[PDB]
Image (cartoon, rainbow over all chains, first blue to last red; front, top):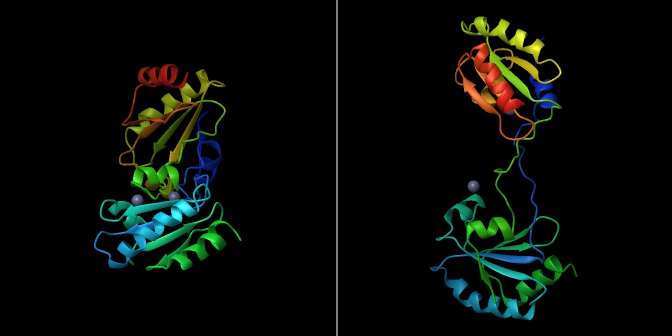
Length: 119
Length: 117
Ligand SMILES: [Zn+2]
Ligand SMILES: [Zn+2]
């Protein structure tokens, strides 16, 4: 005849349907920096050229990404950006490490070496 | 040098971070009907015998399930049930086809032979 179904049975016979929160999973082929900045940020203008030269010095070893929070408000909001700049250090495996505020080249190199490249 | 990212590009190069994938993965070994009913439901009274009949003539081809929404409030709420009866036709692959309202034996056979089989 027809088959009566509890929710517990539904999960086994129909679909294990709950939309469980997704675990962080990096998709890039090299570790990365992700720099959340804005045009009106003072420090960022000094940091900007530092990131360009770091992207050359570590070329082939890392990516350095930039996100303009004004142009990408959904992304910025979803990641709770408050301090400008907010800099993410994203290793191939593990949770991103987050720094709020500006950093010197040597501070950046420190994070690149220890966090991105696992020295 | 540095690479600028749109959100769409972030989703590909960094992390597909939203809970927006989940694939509907039907777990059964044959197609199914799932009938969301309730005791307070008038038209369900007419549909019930029809389903039990269909349950027999298609035995081994499909399953016909029944969910009492008042006994399974989380299921009813999670799937946004808005009227009773609500009937699902669940294919081996693809999203289920959903019909709100009582159907006829002629109509149910329609979906079964065409959508399920
Ligand atoms: Zn979002
Ligand atoms: Zn739920």
